[PDB]
Image (spheres, coloured by chain):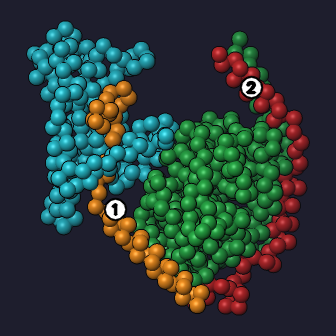
Chain colours: A cyan, B green, C orange, D red
Amino acid sequence: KTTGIVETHFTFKDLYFKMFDVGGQRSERKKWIHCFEGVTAIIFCVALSDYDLVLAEDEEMNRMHESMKLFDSICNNKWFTETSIILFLNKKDLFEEKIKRSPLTICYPEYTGSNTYEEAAAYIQCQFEDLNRRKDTKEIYTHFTCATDTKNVQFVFDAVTDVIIKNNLKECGLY
Amino acid sequence: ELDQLRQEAEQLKNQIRDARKACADATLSQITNNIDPVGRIQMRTRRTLRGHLAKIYAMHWGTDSRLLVSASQDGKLIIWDSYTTNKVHAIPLRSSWVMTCAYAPSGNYVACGGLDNICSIYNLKTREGNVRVSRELAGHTGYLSCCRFLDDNQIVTSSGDTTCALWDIETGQQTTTFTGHTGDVMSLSLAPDTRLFVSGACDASAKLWDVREGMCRQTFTGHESDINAICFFPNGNAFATGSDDATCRLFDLRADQELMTYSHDNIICGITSVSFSKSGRLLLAGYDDFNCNVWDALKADRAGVLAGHDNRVSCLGVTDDGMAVATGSWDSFLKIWN
Amino acid sequence: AEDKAAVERSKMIDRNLREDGEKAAKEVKLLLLGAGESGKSTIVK
Amino acid sequence: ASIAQARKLVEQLKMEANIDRIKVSKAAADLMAYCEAHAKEDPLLTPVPASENPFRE
């Protein structure tokens, strides 16, 4: 019935997770983005199918080039200096199917590689992971996923455990 | 085509500007220059309130100037007692994203709000010995960023939908909708007679609505960034604002003009709360740099400073009788200065 | 008398808040961002 | 399309145009008079020592 923050709860191996889907707020972000200062990590989702063939209700605004802008803005906020990001690249089957017909050069100006799926995915990950400038404080976890992949929960669990461990070493001064 | 309408609007705005530049015979500083100032104002903490565990976002003094109400980024809502620091009530909340709170003039109800885009009323009065949700008011699209009780049955709320509204607590459907702002409304205060109110939004402007006709009648500008706080002068003929430009300004309704600005060259952080003392001689402002300032409304010179918080100050208020000032900060503490 | 009763009420309230905070401190909070029409629904399942 | 919005804005501006305005020198005088009329009862201006102050320990 409610609109605005949406919350989901689940457990895995004696841990409790809380996920906030605040993406339906539809207002100015800058007035409420600081209410989340203290979250363990940020989960980001990017669809590999937008590399081309779909712009967004516009004329020269690529969907991937807007996802990159949002990632750049979010990763470099003043409130998110110490919070790591878990980046999910979804819908790889469509990417593999569309590489054979539509090359990757239509999205980014210079090379991709073999116009082969293995080589384009790595370049996209490298391009998307180079938008952070807080490399001394935060880290990025990337995991290609599809509509059939079923090992995402263990990736999230392990990334959260690693983030917690490194956070404590920092407090103690060790790292 | 539409250019004719643009030209007509420009001509109307030019006429407004010309009419405004006429009553300005004089200045407010010139009239009040030949008077005796107040001097140096020194205040110290008297009571400290502990018990919260997260950032504090709202506060509202009671109508008897004894009990408080505080909202933190948890599901909790504590009714305080500044005379003897013993809590009275603690109300859990469904969504832990509270942004504002209010205390009813009858001392029987409170209110909340936040990113859930819903305002809720709690029966603090005798309800077999506990508190439960009375009504949830839905219909806003964006987050709710202020709310004030008019009576035990009517409440005015402002939201991030660039829209304010007047509700009916007995029915739950809003009876009047105030539109015209192009930005997210951030603040809202009521006049002493409860027949007019003002608002401020993320577009630099302030409007003067009336609860009966439901129409704007005056628009005040002057700031160059978002506006976060607003409150009326005790006489009801003036109000003060606070923006992200580190400046506070004073406006008067009858003259439709801007009187004074309160600023300094050592302040860059924006204001988060604005309040007048009784008789309007002292203006209180809370800033981002952990500090609270006391101004002089008539002459615009600093008269004191308050420094007891280690984090940003998000709210402040003055009792009905003007006997105390309460401050809330982004840590989990409150303080009372006198 | 009344002051005493207020004291026990405050102490019970403080105990309840302490227990609530202790229970809430043991949970992992995740903010799920993402671009529009890109997914963020399959991940939920 | 936007013609209705433009006409509504023009009507609002026209409504705000025809209003009565007093001079600043009178509003300032009234503000000063109110400030000086109630300054004798303003505890934040003069601290009463421990007599009526409820926050003295």
Q: Is B8 above or below relative to B76?
A: above
Q: Which residue is mark 2?
A: D8
Residue ID at (45%, 80%): C11
Front residue of B214 and A111: B214
Coordinates of residue A12 in the picture (x, y in percent): 20, 50
Quarter of the figure that contains the C terminus of chain B: bottom right
Coordinates of residue C13 in the picture (x, y in percent): 46, 74
Q: Is A56 above or below relative to A139?
A: above
Q: Is B85 above or below relative to B250?
A: below
In the image, is D33 to the left or to the right of C44? right
Secondary structure under tag 1 reads helix
Q: Which residue is mark 1?
A: C24
Residue ID at (43%, 52%): A35
The numbered mark 1 sits on a residue in which chain?
A: C
Amino acid type at image mark 2 = Lys
Give how far apart the Cα atoms at labels 1 and 2 are.
51 Å
Secondary structure under tag 2 reads helix
Residue ID at (72%, 54%): B153
